[PDB]
Image 1 (cartoon, chains in turn blue, green):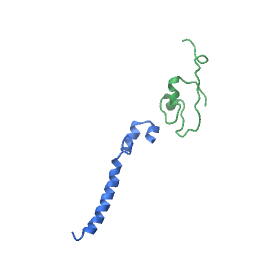
Image 2 (cartoon, chains in turn blue, brown):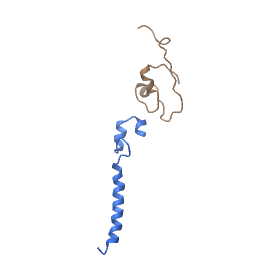
Image 3 (cartoon, helix red, strand yellow):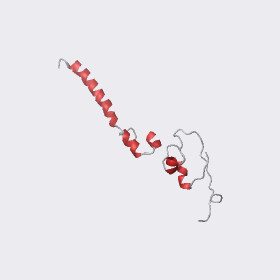
Image 4 (cartoon, chains in turn brown, orange):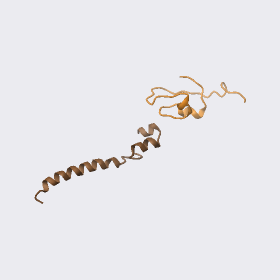
Length: 49
Length: 49
C-alpha cells in the first residue's frame, strides 16, 4: 500500500490500452465489427457505408 | 456510351454493380460522374419470334 502511486500509473495504462483494444469489438451502428465479414455480406456501396 | 439492353439489367448500369452487363458487357467505375439515360424500344428493336 506504500507503492500505490506507481502501481496506479501502470494500472491506468493497462486499463486504457485494454479498453482501446476492446473498442475493436464494438459496432458503432454498423452491421458487424468484423471487417472482412462486412466485405463478404454486401454490395460494395453498402460495405463502404 | 451507347447500346440496347433488356429492362432487368438497367439497375446493373450503376457504380458498384455486378451482374452480366457489369460483369461481361459494360462496366462503370465506382466514382462515375455522369448520367444514365434509357428508353424502351420494343417497337424499334423487337419482332415476332
